[PDB]
Image (cartoon, rainbow over all chains, first blue to last red; front, top):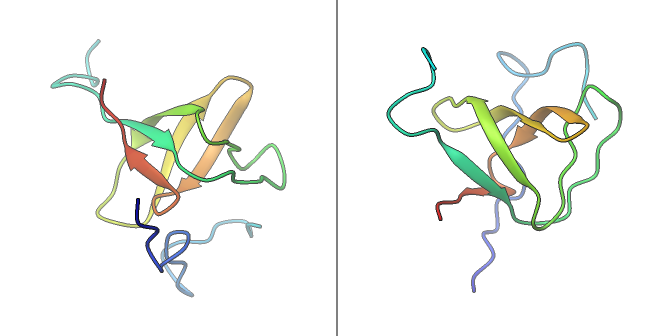
Length: 22
Length: 65
């Protein structure tokens, strides 16, 4: 098995993020 | 039935992810999630038993039995 360095999907300042997430 | 066709994209949780509210979808290594909106790399939305909300695509992997 090999774990990928990039953890969790990307989250830019635009497009994504709605009503604030945590 | 109408929109769901050509085999549905099924994904399986990899690591133990923790939620924050009923708005986010929680899932642990094993819990399967049905995708309802799969975009080109990024955040994917799905549904789960008593758990509904968005979920990362990096902590999940397309599963197929």
